[PDB]
RNA sequence: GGCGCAUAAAGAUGAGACGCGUUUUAGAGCUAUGCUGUUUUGAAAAAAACAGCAUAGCAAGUUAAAAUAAGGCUAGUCCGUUAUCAACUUGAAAAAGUGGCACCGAGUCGGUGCUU
């Protein structure tokens, strides 16, 4: 039985379909497992697979980092206890035990309630003598007297847990800490970045302006007023305002799509800037790094202000002066309140619920809520000056422990610790004998290259241990082999190229890679010298000359710098039409300018032998971060550099990764040529090509050369192969589930291998569907065109961006009110019957772009041919269209489309292009899917190595099946029901297998493998129509869907009519049965049984909701620790039910507590799952259930399908609720009438079906009441939402005489009431009908459990009511 | 106003949101799970009104509707009526 | 679909560190009014509150300790929210195995015939 399989790959579903030769969908009676009356179910062999998406591994990485950092923190506390173990035991024994039980209730505690000092008296005098710990800190640095042991331990014990960022390197000096050198570092970055428009910041004083307190926004324009001028919205201006703490926009600063707001204090910055970076390019991230660094300098000058007794008192005096300003400012403020208002004094100070004082201190609030609360109220107060300066200065009432503590360099804690150790070195000699251990503890830092301290037990770490003892920070060097472990860190952190595996890719800023990309921009340069009329690609003499001149001179090179400084300075040409680069270069030798600026030796950089030396330096400056292994790795290069630049070279860094490896560029060669990719970029003859053609040169060796490496060596199983891929995790989950569905699928049909496997896959978009993300872009095209013209069309008719998407008006604004074909003026009001004709008609390429469609009055203004537009028009209009050329109204591609009449007509290369745009599969991961499905199915070798390729792997593109679907009107409303995916995969099989029937002769372009290389250099006829049943040519017309039609309309009303039942000439076998295929396939798509399987899951993830709630006494809380009361200590709430167990047991009924045989649902947390697997029956007797019956323990996961009366299918949501399962069988004429009802204003084609489909919409008003009938008498069987149903029926009866379009739109919105999964809300015309779910679960006990296979073709039906 | 407006800030309140939708599956039913339970909440995207405007248009009010289990959730959403409008 | 310049881009991935935030406790609340409690002089009320309670008015109000997914054993200054998954058949797992074909019609698949 010959058959083939259609598939479709999204990210939540996969469509699977089985077709036969006449495209009749098969159907089989099936075996039923369980205990029902029915023992066979006839099912159609077509459906889809639904499943929840596959999340990335980011959150688990973050919580892993959090657990590790709290682990190291607590173990630092354990270290400090280890040093002060004995002497603290000398004075007071249970002190550390008091610190251990600081968290309990005094009932639960077994020592004194006062942790510090034991008594009441020294504790009260402790808080009165020292209110904070900072007073104690500044006391202990500025002391001569002895102090208490537990006091000093508590001091330095505070000094360990909070140590500030290690992100500065070195010590505190104006090279890295003052605002002047870092500000001028930013200045050199800015002017040295641009090289044009040089600004000055020499005589200005950013220390005096930025350092002293004032208003921030008032400070903002002042530094603008000290520089000569950029703007108040300058890039430097918004940059420095960003560095102060204001969060500016950067939309108009770079002319980007959306707004570009960044908050440095927000945690979004560390990737949101990255998404900003992807809209500007990588050249600016160092400038943003300098902005962040200078912002840290501003914050450091903000926190340190005291400078009088600066001898070892940098911090604590500033903190306690801030404490005092809080104190006296509170007193004067309260005196101002009671002095002025005896109302709202309680609302400020006794509230803790309205963002007041008590909320900012004792309640739950923040400083934004408090300042935003008090600011009009304090503004209302009668006499109140010199406090708004604290409002704009953030100075009033500000606490100690804030979010601005993230600025603190650890050296302040280091030396501040250190002076305390100097004042205490004399009294307590243990400190004197342990001080290097103390500063060693504080200054410890696990490097990047080391990684975690495993013992081979991790999944993630790679440490090797040169000695074998406990890894301790006293003697950290005694264990670590940095060479071997860091060598693994070189190996564990490099990536492998897909385009060249078994090899390590390059860093991003390699000199080799930058030569690759600068040459990859210069390979597209095709310049016209004025007098040859020839855009000629460059020579290696020319390219090497320019690289010798310009790319070794400056980074950002414009075209006027280019043609001025080369073509006239060297070559003496005035105007050269350099067609490739518009203004500036996408690639630049920035690292070349870096190191050439550093070591100042052009001979050293132009050596061919120091290149791999620079690969070592680029590699080490790429990877490592800890400076010691930075410098020793270049002690190998201690010879070349005489230590001056090595005072600087260790600082400079580079991040990123190249997409290629050196063995793919400067590795393999053409054996015919003996040339690397660099050699082709410096010598590609007359035809200099881009690297995408260097891969895809099918005549040349490089597709074979890469492809012999793309095949694996010793291949692993399926799972590691899927782990080798490149995409989202969810698309990989779609690949794996696709393979599983193919596996069970071929296990269904006789265990016979299939014949053709078609794949469609396109996903991962977030571009907001281009409704309003495009009118600003094409409106910007209007503003550029009108900007160059000056013929102000926007003075007599300005239009709106809701109506800018419609192509008629937009094409009217494109051509400056002048028609292309006839030199005439297109009138304003007659745009309705104005015609939209294509450059190349609808028989050669299905194109709806701007690049093809132009606006005119008549179709006959073009000429008389389906060929290129007539030479009585282009030669006629070679002036105004060249004005469109000079003003950039058209691209060069659309230019040669319009000036294709220069080429006479459509050539072999033309139809070569139009055929090779329909079918060339250009997604990498799609070809990988084709390889993985290729490996499993075809496995019969021969005596040779030949894969006997019985199974064809056909890959299509969405334009073919999509435009087939739209042309033959088999419409697709994504919102009726989930059946549409299976119909999409079915049509994928239709178009794919129709291609393998009609054209087997060029299977080698849309099937992976090695078929015949016979192509369209001879399959295109060099003349008109080939003869009947004697055609060696493919066809004439570049569309491949023409033979499904009846009429092939030419550009003259001419019906090219192709034969009815299509065959193939070389086979003599029929390929298209036009007489019955559309009633057949239309009968297929209207089928009421389509296999829908929502895939089951075991719910994993986090334990519960994480925000810790206060100590109430509700009995549904989960304790944080096992010794902690959920009442007397609080805890978490709302756990995560992994899966629901179904249990028969006996509860103790009534006051007599007698065994009552029940069968009830029970939810399971994830926090009890491993306990449930370890012993379930002891867990359930621990739950309070007796007489467990283990053979009736029914594990019911999430989305386990249940069946009720009339086939009322419902999906099991969790233990607490249900979800809704049955589907909708809709006749296809209703689907089409809702489609064209929805598409009435956006029909997008010829007026024949605009009027035809329009009147056809106007026919069937009956269909609307038939659809509401279907939802009516359908919804009473399975939904049972009675009041909602009467609301929508009555509301439907109200607005019956509505305008048709939006009425049908509200019908489409009314279809959500049926759909699968969660209950939703929706809005018929104005009345938004509220959702309604089913929290009940008692009915499922009396229902039909169904277990499903992964294709839903082995149902297993279990009845709960038959169970005892 | 954006999608990751709602994702990040409703993420910041102690709920879980993990939407699922891309081409060609032209549906973007985000999931809410107002209780960590089978009481998940859902809004789609359809052709006329983006899911931001579906969200704020669906939650200008408090909780006042039928179910007595979700109301604090709606109160949470009440706060995020006002933050994105005046930032 | 965006073909967005006929071209087609960019991808999972894992190591370091801060800063919060949250929660419980320590941060003795003071005075006046009224109440429950034992004393006190008492054949019973009767202050001495030492306490607790509630209500008013006052008073201060910034910080610390601990934990930060339950915990696990392999006990490491490691790991625990990723991917992975119907059922029954064995098998510790790893895994492997488990179900006829044509024809007719279509309201969630049903019916007919044959092979058994």
Image (spheres, grey):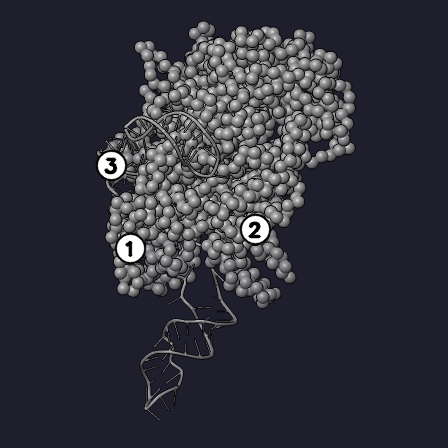
Secondary structure under tag 1 reads strand
Residue placed furthest toward the top: A672
- Tag 3 subunit: A
Front-lying residue, A774 or C1: C1
> Is A1150 placed above or below A1306 here?
below
Marker count (numbered):
3
Residue ID for mark 2: A1287
Secondary structure under tag 3 reads loop
Residue ID for mark 1: A1157
Asked whether, in this view, residue A158 is left or right of residue A964, the answer is: left
Residue ID for mark 3: A469
Front-lying residue, A787 or A415: A787
Q: Is residue A721 visible?
A: yes
Q: Earlier in the sequence, mark 2 or mark 1?
A: 1
Q: Using a 10 Å C-alpha cutoff, classify the residue at mark 1 as few (fewer than 14 neighbours), some (14 to 19) or many (20 or more).
A: some
Q: Using a 10 Å C-alpha cutoff, classify the residue at mark 3 as few (fewer than 14 neighbours), some (14 to 19) or many (20 or more).
A: few
Front-lying residue, A1115 or A1286: A1286
- Tag 1 subunit: A
Q: On the same chain: label 2 and label 1?
A: yes
Front-lying residue, C3 or A40: A40
Measuring from the top left, give residue A609's x and y in whole percent.
43, 13
Measuring from the top left, give residue A55's x and y in whole percent.
43, 36
Measuring from the top left, give residue A626's x and y in whole percent.
40, 32
The CA distance from mark 2 to mark 3 is 76 Å
Circle on res. A701: none
Q: Earlier in the sequence, mark 3 or mark 1?
A: 3
- Tag 2 subunit: A
Q: On the same chain: label 2 and label 3?
A: yes
For image coordinates 33% across by 57% down, the residue present is: A1125
The CA distance from mark 2 to mark 1 is 43 Å
């Amino acid at each position: 039985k010959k058959y083939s399989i259609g598939l479709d790959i999204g990210t939540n579903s996969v469509g699977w379909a089985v077709i036969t030769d006449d495209y009749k969908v098969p159907s089989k009676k099936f075996k039923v497992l369980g205990n029902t009356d029915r023992h066979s179910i006839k099912k159609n062999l077509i459906g889809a697979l639904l499943f929840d998406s596959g999340e990335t591994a980011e959150a688990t990485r973050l919580k892993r980092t959090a657990r590790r950092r709290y682990t190291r923190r607590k173990n630092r506390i354990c270290y400090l206890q280890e040093i002060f173990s004995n002497e603290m035991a000398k004075v007071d024994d249970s002190f550390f035990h008091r610190l251990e039980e600081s968290f309990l209730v005094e009932e639960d505690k077994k020592h004194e309630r006062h942790p510090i000092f034991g008594n009441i008296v020294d504790e009260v005098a402790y808080h009165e003598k020292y209110p904070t710990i900072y007073h104690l800190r500044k006391k202990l640095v500025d002391s001569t007297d002895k102090a208490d042991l537990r006091l000093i331990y508590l001091a330095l014990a505070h000094m360990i847990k909070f140590r500030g960022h290690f992100l500065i390197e070195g010590d505190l000096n104006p090279d890295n800490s003052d605002v002047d050198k870092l500000f001028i570092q930013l200045v050199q970055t800015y002017n040295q970045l641009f090289e044009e428009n040089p600004i000055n910041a020499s005589g200005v004083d950013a220390k005096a302006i930025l350092s002293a307190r004032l208003s921030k926004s008032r400070r903002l324009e002042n530094l603008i007023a000290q520089l000569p001028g950029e703007k108040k919205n300058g890039l430097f201006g918004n940059l420095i305002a960003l560095s102060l703490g204001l969060t500016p926009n950067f939309k108009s600063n770079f002319d980007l799509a959306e707004d570009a707001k960044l908050q440095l204090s927000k945690d979004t910055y560390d990737d949101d800037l990255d998404n900003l970076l992807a809209q500007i390019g990588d050249q600016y991230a160092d400038l943003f790094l300098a902005a962040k660094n200078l912002s840290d300098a501003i914050l450091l000058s903000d926190i340190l202000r005291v400078n009088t007794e600066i001898t070892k008192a940098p911090l604590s005096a500033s903190m306690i002066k801030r404490y005092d300003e809080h104190h006296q400012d509170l007193t004067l403020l309260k005196a101002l309140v009671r002095q002025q208002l005896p109302e709202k004094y309680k609302e400020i100070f006794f509230d803790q619920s309205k963002n007041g004082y008590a909320g900012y201190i004792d309640g739950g609030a923040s400083q934004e809520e408090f300042y935003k609360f008090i600011k009009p109220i304090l503004e209302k107060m009668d006499g109140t000056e010199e406090l708004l300066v604290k409002l704009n200065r953030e100075d009033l009432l500000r606490k100690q422990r804030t979010f601005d503590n993230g600025s603190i360099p650890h050296q302040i804690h280091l030396g501040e610790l250190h002076a305390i150790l100097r004042r205490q070195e004399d009294f307590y000699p243990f400190l004197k004998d342990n001080r290097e251990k103390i500063e060693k503890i504080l200054t410890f830092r696990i490097p990047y290259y080391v990684g975690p301290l495993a013992r081979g037990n991790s999944r993630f770490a790679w440490m090797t241990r040169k000695s074998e003892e406990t890894i301790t920070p006293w003697n950290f060097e005694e264990v670590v082999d940095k060479g071997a472990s860091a060598q693994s860190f070189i190996e564990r952190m490099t990536n492998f190229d897909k385009n060249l595996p078994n090899e390590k890719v390059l860093p991003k800023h390699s000199l080799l890679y930058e030569y690759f990309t600068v040459y990859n921009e210069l390979t597209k340069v095709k310049y016209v010298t004025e007098g040859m009329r020839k855009p000629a690609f460059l020579s290696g003499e020319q390219k090497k000359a320019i690289v010798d001149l310009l790319f070794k001179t400056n980074r950002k090179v414009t075209v006027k710098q280019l043609k001025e400084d080369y073509f006239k300075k060297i070559e003496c040409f005035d105007s050269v039409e350099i067609s490739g680069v518009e203004d500036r270069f996408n690639a630049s030798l920035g690292t070349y300018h870096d190191l050439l600026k550093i070591i100042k030796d052009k001979d050293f950089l132009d050596n061919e032998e120091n290149e791999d030396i620079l690969e070592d330096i680029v590699l080490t400056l790429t990877l490592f971060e800890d400076r010691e292994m930075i410098e020793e790795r270049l002690k190998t290069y201690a010879h070349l550099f005489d230590d001056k630049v090595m005072k600087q070279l260790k600082r400079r860094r580079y991040t990123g990764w190249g997409r290629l490896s050196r063995k793919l560029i400067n590795g393999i060669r053409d054996k015919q040529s003996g040339k690397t990719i660099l050699d082709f970029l410096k010598s590609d003859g007359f035809a200099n090509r881009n690297f995408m053609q260097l891969i895809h040169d099918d005549s040349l060796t490089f597709k074979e050369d890469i492809q012999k490496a793309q095949v694996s060596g010793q291949g692993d199983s399926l799972h590691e192969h899927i782990a080798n891929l490149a995409g989202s995790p969810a698309i990989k989950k779609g690949i794996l589930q696709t393979v599983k569905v193919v596996d069970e699928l071929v296990k269904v049909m006789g265990r016979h291998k299939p014949e053709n496997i078609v794949i469609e896959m396109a996903r991962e978009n977030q571009t907001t569907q281009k409704g309003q993300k495009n009118s600003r872009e094409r409106m910007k095209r209007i503003e550029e065109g009108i900007k160059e013209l000056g013929s102000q069309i926007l003075k007599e008719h300005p239009v709106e961006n809701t109506q800018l998407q419609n192509e008629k008006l937009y094409l009217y604004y494109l051509q400056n009110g002048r028609d292309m074909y006839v030199d005439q003026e297109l009138d304003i009001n007659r745009l309705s019957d104005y015609d939209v004709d294509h450059i190349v008609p609808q028989s050669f390429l299905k194109d709806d772009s701007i690049d093809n469609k132009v606006l005119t009055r008549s179709d006959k203004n073009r000429g008389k041919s389906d060929n290129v537009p007539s030479e009585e028009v282009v030669k006629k209009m070679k002036n105004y269209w060249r004005q469109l050329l000079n003003a950039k109204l058209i691209t060069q591609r659309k230019f040669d489309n319009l000036t294709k009449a220069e080429r006479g007509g459509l050539s072999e290369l033309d139809k070569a292009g139009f055929i090779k745009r329909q079918l060339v599969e250009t997604r990498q991961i799609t070809k990988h899917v084709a390889q993985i499905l290729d490996s499993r199915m075809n496995t019969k070798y021969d005596e040779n190595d030949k894969l006997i390729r019985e199974v064809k792997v056909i890959t299509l593109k969405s334009k073919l099946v999509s435009d087939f679907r739209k042309d033959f009107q088999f419409y697709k409303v994504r919102e009726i029901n989930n059946y549409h995916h299976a119909h999409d995969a079915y049509l994928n099989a239709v178009v794919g297998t129709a291609l393998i029937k009609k054209y087997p002769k060029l299977e080698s372009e849309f099937v992976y493998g090695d078929y015949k290389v016979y192509d369209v250099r001879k399959m295109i006829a060099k003349s008109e129509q080939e003869i009947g049943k004697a055609t060696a040519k493919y066809f004439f017309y570049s569309n491949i869907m023409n033979f499904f039609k009846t009429e092939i309309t030419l550009a003259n009303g001419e019906i090219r009519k192709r034969p009815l039942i299509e065959t193939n000439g070389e086979t003599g076998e029929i390929v298209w049965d036009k007489g019955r295929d559309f009633a057949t396939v239309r009968k297929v798509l209207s089928m009421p049984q389509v296999n829908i399987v929502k895939k089951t899951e075991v719910q994993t993830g986090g334990f519960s909701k994480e925000s810790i709630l206060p100590k109430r006494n509700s009995d549904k809380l989960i304790a944080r620790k096992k010794d902690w009361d959920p009442k007397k200590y609080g805890g978490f709430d709302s756990p995560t039910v992994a899966y629901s167990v179904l249990v028969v047991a006996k509860v103790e009924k009534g006051k007599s507590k007698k065994l009552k045989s029940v069968k009830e649902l029970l939810g399971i947390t994830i926090m009890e799952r491993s306990s449930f697997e370890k012993n379930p029956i002891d867990f359930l007797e621990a739950k309070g259930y007796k007489e467990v019956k283990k053979d009736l323990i029914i594990k019911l996961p999430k989305y386990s399908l249940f069946e009720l009366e009339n086939g009322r299918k419902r999906m099991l949501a969790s233990a607490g609720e249900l979800q809704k399962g049955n589907e909708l069988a809709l006749p296809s004429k209703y689907v089409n009438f809702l489609y064209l009802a929805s598409h009435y204003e956006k029909l997008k084609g010829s007026p024949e079906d605009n009027e035809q489909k329009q009147l056809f919409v106007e026919q069937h008003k009956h269909y609307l009441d038939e659809i509401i009938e279907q939802i009516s008498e359908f919804s009473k069987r399975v939904i049972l939402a009675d009041a909602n149903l009467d609301k929508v029926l009555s509301a439907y009866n109200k607005h019956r005489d509505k305008p048709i379009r939006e009425q049908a739109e509200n019908i489409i919105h009314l279809f959500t009431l049926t759909n699968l999964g969660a209950p939703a809300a929706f809005k018929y015309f104005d009345t938004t009908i509220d959702r309604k779910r089913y929290t009940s679960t008692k009915e499922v006990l009396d229902a039909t459990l169904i277990h499903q296979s992964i294709t839903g073709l082995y149902e297993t039906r279990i009845d709960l009511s038959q169970l005892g | 106003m954006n999608i990751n407006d709602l994702i990040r800030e409703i993420k910041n309140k102690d709920y879980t949101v993990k939407l699922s939708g891309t081409d060609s599956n032209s549906i973007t039913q985000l999931i809410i799970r107002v209780n960590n339970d089978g009481n998940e909440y859902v809004i789609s995207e359809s052709e006329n009104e983006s899911i931001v405007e579906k969200f704020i248009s669906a939650f200008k009010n408090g909780w006042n509707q039928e179910y007595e289990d979700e109301e604090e959730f709606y109160n949470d959403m009440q706060t995020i009526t006002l933050k994105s409008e005046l930032n």
